[PDB]
Image (tube, rainbow over all chains, first blue to last red; front, side):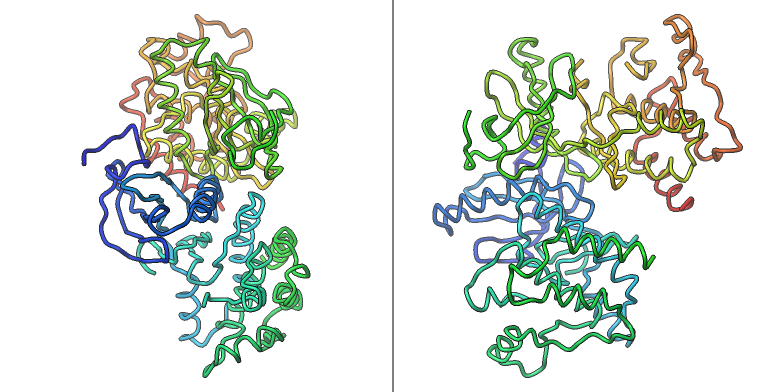
Length: 270
Length: 268
């Protein structure tokens, strides 16, 4: 099909698909380049007709409409969404950045810890991102190290694809997932708490080895995680983690509060 | 006009107009509130059926469709555009805090120069915004301190109050020759704005300023040189190449962004 510059990012003719890089319940994801400007992008084809009922389709369209309105230094961009060839086509940023997963297993090999000062540098940006998202009534739904990208310069980008430009049972299970299959805005806070623990501890709070799913549910119920070392990490980091990893969603702080703490701690640690 | 959550940001019903904040040749801008999320927005109403012929209507629609694709932290986001009550309605990111115009005046009244460190801190963000617009083949057409918003956190938001892009603050040579507006016309504006950040006045400003003297000063690019004691050769040379009568010899925004990024990294 022939180029149509008037359409910009809103037609498949302006993209060359490279390879499939992902399959989901409802979607396939590709690496593509825009033909107008040569920018590498992720192209998510969602079967809103062939794989969803009417309720799923409408809710998914509403959600993508909100996501492509976000405009924040620390969020992976949704560049476009349009219907063509009977699918919802979503064009997303692939960032020139490593995922926090990679950085974590790096420090692990080198038997070193991320100093509290760097942790706050990264965590304040994630919190800035999530505050932006919750202010437009958008839940993230999969906060994990694989979805957090860090640039050359140390700017954080939160995505939901787990795919950078160059390198690539949900990861942190909440009590409300275990018990009621529920996910709300406070479920993002739970995950954010677990990610702050993982940056300091270099492993998930509910990690273990053998690990029955049943043992993993028992530990989550009791919030039974190894305490962080009080010699390496302030009481205010360890407390923020404890407030976030709370079995009751209602008792977890809102992201405004977590962002405010991250901002005070960035300020007094830099 | 009563609520409809299903219709989203795409009908006037889900918005309360709170006051006018802008007026252009073909448009009014309002501060408004989304009743679905309590988020405050700007609402531009464009008179595509009363002040416009078919050509201008079709051009203005094509442009709005390209503008709503822009997505950059330093560019005012366009959330939605729809036709309702016989206008083209646009729902935009509101930047209701300050702007470069208010900052420049603040420094002017305090009889203080803006430190070069601070100039690059704001200027690299404006360059970032414009590199994004140009990469998508979108001209700004109305670059001036008042259209450069600044959030509480000090994030630059490049906007356009009253779509002055369809119609200046910075008389360019390609206005004096009537010649019309292109990508390198944005670069002229950009160089004048950098100058004004360092001098606290437009490069062609005068007390008893009048069209004759202005046309002469643009013809010769006659602006008071910046104090070499306060502002680097790099900053002065970057102003110098942008303020050039020939659009084809002005640098492209990628080059200006690259210098700004490198000058920012150095002075911090």
